[PDB]
Length: 307
Length: 306
Image (tube, rainbow over all chains, first blue to last red):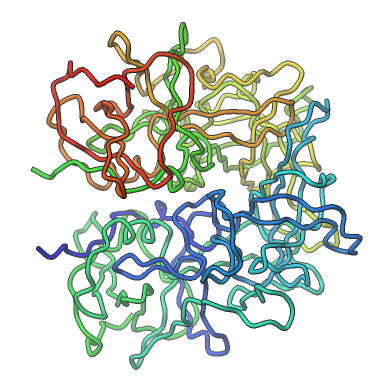
């Protein structure tokens, strides 16, 4: 008995980004000529193998948990956070992982709120500090078990069990948001380890199709766009189903149930990403009620209908 | 007939459906004299969502819309004119208690409001800490508006805004009451379209909850939020839509390595679990275990005691 492969039935307004906790807003395609596309969150094979720093919960993506240090006396990261995995499991740096699960996989400033010991303090927001976690910081060393926290609203308490809840991205004069550049998980000038592989098209006329979110920008005017290979719900679905991949390429179609007609077709690669026959950098427009659907296994030679 | 199933997810692989946080514990209580009628995390076993329940973790206790002009109110300095979290237009005539994901407790929800992106040398320029009290007279989400009380930074008027939840606050006059519903239209108007109240209706049984210890941002006590089924079960039932064969699915919490059943429970068609137990306490489970569907049983099926 061979279990058939399937996608969940979810419209674009029913999908979550697997690289930042936000709904999908757009589908987007680009040749990405001058970058290497190698995200570490939102990585799952079609047969259900999680890779990189990928885990199952939306709440763990770009989240951190652990114990704060004593003050560092550093100009930027006034405290460190000694990490456990988001599920609370002890983190062993010798694990065959790039970093704890859910660690941010871009170079940029992640903004969110650190919460620590409940306080009898009579102040509003007493136990909620706004913090910047820059993955260009010299103290961003999650592979080693520690990251730097730069407080921006309130004061971080030393030596307390703490949770970081992500909210958005900040950009400053020396820290552009670079979604396709990985952090150096062990610190400046070190080599990343245990990475999910880079992805790209391998058929003439094809480009990757991404699930895109415009996430909150808390400093700077540039809209912050984060592209994932598959949405978090697909990670969860493939993990659950673990259907055997019967070829290297699944043919999927985007259907409009209002008309019963498909809008476009695409290849969903066994590695866990989508390509389409398209050129240029632009959104791919879909009807709000439409959804992706698995139609059949095909092979590397299947020529897609162009968009 | 399509077989009913539960997803294979351990306790550390589950999300609270009433607040965006991982499940920390299973927990049981008699909840004496208290009506348990949450509106998030509500889904029947054949995949019908109820109350304000929707599918995304990111929409739970989140809000989206346009801020008003300054109100000059003592507490809610701005209103937020709501759409649903997915951006779909909301209107009060929808057959829902309130926009999807609206908080379903009486208390202060703390989080961050983000608005128009703008170039600035100021850190956190476009991220304001805000309290959304569901006990406020301005908390009328069924009518399309809620009140925002700023606590960190200044809210901008007339801007498209998103609220990202972070935790719960207890201030001088707002105890947290997880089982008391907002008056979604204000106290003078009845709530509508509610997912039904749940309870054991069986001597010696209690509800088993999926519990999260969520961030407590003001007040010295920890805050616990209990849901009837985790968000992943809502998602699973919605997709599968397996027809129910009775009112009660017998389920067993199993350890897949030892092969042992830890306990059995009744998963009710309405979308909640009961166990044969008395008292208020955690229900301890192996970290590698999970509920497994056993069989559909009679609506009056009796359980082995915990």
